[PDB]
Image (cartoon, coloured by chain):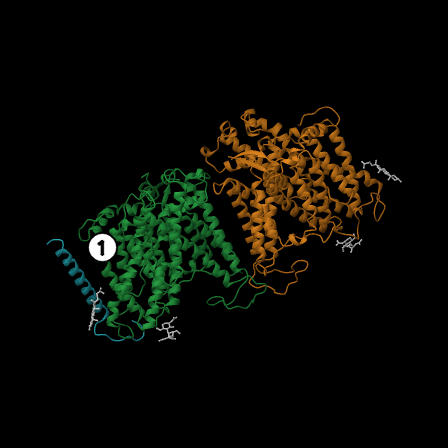
Chain colours: A green, B orange, C cyan
Amino acid sequence: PLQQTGQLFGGLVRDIRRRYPYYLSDITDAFSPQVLAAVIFIYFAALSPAITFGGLLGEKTRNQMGVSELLISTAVQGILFALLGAQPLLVVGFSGPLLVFEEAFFSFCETNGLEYIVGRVWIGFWLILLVVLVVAFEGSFLVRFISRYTQEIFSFLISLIFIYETFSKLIKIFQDHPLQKTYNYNVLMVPKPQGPLPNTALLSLVLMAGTFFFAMMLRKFKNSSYFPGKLRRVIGDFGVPISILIMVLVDFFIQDTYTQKLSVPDGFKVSNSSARGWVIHPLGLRSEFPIWMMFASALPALLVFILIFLESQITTLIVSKPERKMVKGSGFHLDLLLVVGMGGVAALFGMPWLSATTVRSVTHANALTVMGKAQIQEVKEQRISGLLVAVLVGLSILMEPILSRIPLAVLFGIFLYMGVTSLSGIQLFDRILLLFKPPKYHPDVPYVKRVKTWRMHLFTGIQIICLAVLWVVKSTPASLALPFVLILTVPLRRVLLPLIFRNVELQCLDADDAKAT
Amino acid sequence: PLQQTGQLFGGLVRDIRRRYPYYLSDITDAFSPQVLAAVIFIYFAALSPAITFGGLLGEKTRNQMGVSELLISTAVQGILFALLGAQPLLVVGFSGPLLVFEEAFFSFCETNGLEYIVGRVWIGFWLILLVVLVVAFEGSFLVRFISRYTQEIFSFLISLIFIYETFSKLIKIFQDHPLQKTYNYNVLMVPKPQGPLPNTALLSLVLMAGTFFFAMMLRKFKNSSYFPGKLRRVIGDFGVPISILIMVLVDFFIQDTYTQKLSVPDGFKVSNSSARGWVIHPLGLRSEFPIWMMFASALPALLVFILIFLESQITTLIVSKPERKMVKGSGFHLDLLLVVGMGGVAALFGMPWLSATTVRSVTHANALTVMGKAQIQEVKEQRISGLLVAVLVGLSILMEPILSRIPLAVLFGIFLYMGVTSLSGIQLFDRILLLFKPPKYHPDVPYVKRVKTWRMHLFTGIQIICLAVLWVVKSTPASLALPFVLILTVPLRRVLLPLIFRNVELQCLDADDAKAT
Amino acid sequence: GERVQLAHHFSEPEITLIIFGVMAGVIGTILLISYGIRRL
Ligand SMILES: *[C@@H]1O[C@H](CO)[C@@H](O[C@@H]2O[C@H](CO)[C@@H](O)[C@H](O)[C@H]2NC(C)=O)[C@H](O)[C@H]1NC(C)=O
Ligand SMILES: *[C@@H]1O[C@H](CO)[C@@H](O[C@@H]2O[C@H](CO)[C@@H](O)[C@H](O)[C@H]2NC(C)=O)[C@H](O)[C@H]1NC(C)=O
Ligand SMILES: CC(C)CCC[C@@H](C)[C@H]1CC[C@H]2[C@@H]3CC=C4C[C@@H](O)CC[C@]4(C)[C@H]3CC[C@]12C
Ligand SMILES: CC(C)CCC[C@@H](C)[C@H]1CC[C@H]2[C@@H]3CC=C4C[C@@H](O)CC[C@]4(C)[C@H]3CC[C@]12C
């Protein structure tokens, strides 16, 4: 799949012939309750970050783009990506670096007195130009230089950021309602409470902890030996839906204590009806858009294309590892083309562009995985799950009473569960646990039985320096350079690492298929 | 150990000849950190029931016997039992049936206008007569007819009672401070809060959950493969103290929220100095004691003797099973005599009689239990742990500033950990789990491979009926008949069960040494 | 659109068709140039 054919649009054509013969199987393979359970999981797992990012975007852009635009864009992109993409297990949605870029570009437009949404339209116009040349010249073949080293480092960093944000939301909630000896019983609640309230933060913490505990207990119950095997598998597959329903009922039976709930726009309308409509004129809405800025948008377009390309290709590599039993194939050129084109088109509608998010797609791949009688047996590869998730995201506005009674603490526990279960397929985390284990308890793997313990610890600690450097960049205003620092790890693997490690050691520590050299 | 010698006081000297030769080992074996961790565990595990039962007894008897008297009696009896008993791993203290008898005797004395404490003195006087005759005629030889059936039924029932009361205390905490939209900020705090308080029950739930979670996590870390083995096992032995310290610091750093703490007497004084003193005259304090009640106390003395005898002897059977690697010997005749005699002596001082509680003794034995590389390896059989626990219980009054900063919720999590770790040595609990397992997943044990599945399930179901009946007996006003109903299972095992079960099935299912008939 | 917007000579479909045509022409020119190279 990563081979360079040399023909114009060669990768795009082969990705079509690789997967579209399996289109009939991509619908029939979804006839199982596990697919429905994965749908219920991924629906919340994509909706809640979408709602949070839409609210933040509306706050930071004066509601030029808000929750409704992001929800509609996510639904459309998910539907079209599931119906046409070669890797139906991927989940396309908004990400953190996209939010940082949008904040920076909004600040730049405010400083220069330019219209922000028209700038987004022009950047997306240049986004469509960039992707076509990359697909035509098979520019997606450079991802074969991204080995297990960079993939696992990126996955571990993204999981750490996910867990850190999950805990930071709880910390913010606790700061909003500190434990006090006395409280004011007359506090306004609309749109949000204006003062600390009793039992709120503690009940949110209890709900989050209970959600995580029930999810982990049901996941263990899937691998347990209790109840009939069919019923045991059915209960384990629906472990996250069962835990979510249990905690929702627990909060519903408590009336007096307030808990923050999911909030969606009232209808299918733009966040700011006084700012822009559904279609934004590329020539300018209020003032004539400058000619120079139309051409000057290429560099932000280049940055956005780099972000989307790296995120999507690394996610597709991670979800399609040979050890995960992906026996249907993935298309790097088709998925990238679809994602970037949908982002460029949705920019014309005043909607944000998206990317193949690591956490959501990794969870979708893991939720569809069926274990053998410890060993991965097969994965329910189908297009129905992503299509249904996108449809439910689009209809989330219409089902507000169901969402209006769902606390975010349950979603916080679910996010923690996703973060802790996304590390199963990463050997970097496994080797980090080997930093706290005696050598005689190490597993029988080629990178342990053929590599000295101190050498393996040194190799692991080399990545820890890279992880710390990436974390520092995230904690700086120049966080948009994170993909470049991530790219710089590839020269470290191909140039600097052989200076201190042998070929056999590098083959054992970094194997593309986890083989014994 | 349960054979009848035929000599007067023959079983007494035989128990003396068995354990006392190992006296020097009983002091040298305790020079290890695991013994210190066991001391720290059992100190709270015996002080908190002592405080709670002393408070309840003082409330129900108008402080004629209270917390200070119970602590002093616990210290004295524990010191004497650790310095003289042949099973030093037993924990001596107050229990629920003793509290029920105290309530019943106080009601009987109040109805008949009798002096409660003088009646207690006379009953304790009658207790010394009963146990001297029983030991002289080797009345402890009847314990050999209590098989694994009755032992496991009593242990499972007592563990269920302990866990249910641990949860009922949390229910009481929730009911006293319910979750309300508004609270009164002006509520009197002395001696206890007079109204619901914000964040109290939720923070107590957080503390209890954290304590139980960290205790279980460190117990698992004991058996994990992380860290060097010596440090790992040291931390695992000190799992309970570390969890207690973490949760105590967590509660200490929260100042505004009120949490219920341990309360100890101000000094070594009687709870009611206006009613009685340290020494109670058997002839009467306020009025002349009737002659007929001196002889009529024999029947309550018989009931108390039956309760104490059955409780202590079944506890000794449970803590000294051959499968628990107790290779130093236990004394049935000597320990029963010492316990009943110390109870009779403490009755003369206005202090409650004590008996070997099952939960605390089993936790104490499991705290000194060493697990091999799974399989039980050895038990640190030494006398220092019980003596130190008794001394610390006695000194608990003098260390009020330390005990006043410990919340009850941490102790509730500790009680939950004790209850869930008390079910390990019960094959009845293991068979209960097999009711929800497919037959092929059942372990390779003699009672499964030699008896049909439905026969074993019927055998388990008969025991659950006895457990449910005993649960009914506890929840009825005639709860003092519980030892007789437990005794009634001995005819069930030896008469009624052979009519429906074959001899091989009875030998496999009820085996004293877990052998294959 | 919404509220009051500045009037342009080309409407939104017209301007987006012009932009797409220019983009297609540039892409075709680049592809034809690349086809010219690697042959002579
Ligand atoms: C919707 O957009 C309008 C402008 O398009 C916002 O109105 C501006 O609000 C900012 C913030 O106070 C100020 O500059 C002025 O009050 C307004 N300026 C102009 C030129 O109208 C409005 O705030 C936006 N609505 C929301 C909810 O953010
Ligand atoms: C200590 O004991 C005395 C007497 O035994 C208690 O005084 C009695 O209190 C009850 C409760 O109201 C009533 O019967 C009378 O007020 C008192 N009766 C007699 C005969 O004195 C006193 O309450 C006890 N103290 C505590 C703290 O319980
Ligand atoms: C990659 C895509 C976006 C094409 C690259 C953009 C450049 C080459 C093209 C695309 C559309 C073009 C615009 C189309 C229409 C007009 C109106 C005219 O009165 C002045 C020039 C102006 C404003 C053009 C300037 C150049 C322009 C912005
Ligand atoms: C089983 C133990 C308690 C001993 C048996 C108790 C009976 C047999 C004995 C022990 C002590 C005895 C009491 C000792 C002293 C006196 C005072 C005297 O002026 C009247 C008789 C009286 C009140 C005795 C009655 C009988 C008595 C109560």
Q: Residue at x 14, y 55 (%)?
A: C35
Image location (x, y in percent) of residue B461: 55, 35
Image location (x, y in percent) of residue B199: 57, 59
Q: Nearer the viewer, residue C29 or C7?
A: C29
Which corner quadrant of the image does residue A435 belong to? top left
- In the rendered image of this protein, does residue B336 appear above or below residue B395? above
Query: Which residue is label 1 attached to?
Result: A135
Badge 1 amino acid:
Val
Q: How many marks?
A: 1
Hey, which residue is sitting farthest front in the picture? Answer: A499
Image location (x, y in percent) of residue B467: 60, 38
Q: Nearer the viewer, residue B191 or B374?
A: B374
Image location (x, y in percent) of residue A112: 31, 73
- In the rendered image of this protein, does residue B289 appear above or below residue C1? above
Q: Quadrant of ligand 1?
A: bottom left
Q: Nearer the viewer, residue A38 or A119?
A: A119
| Left or right: A52 as drawn, with respect to B177 | left
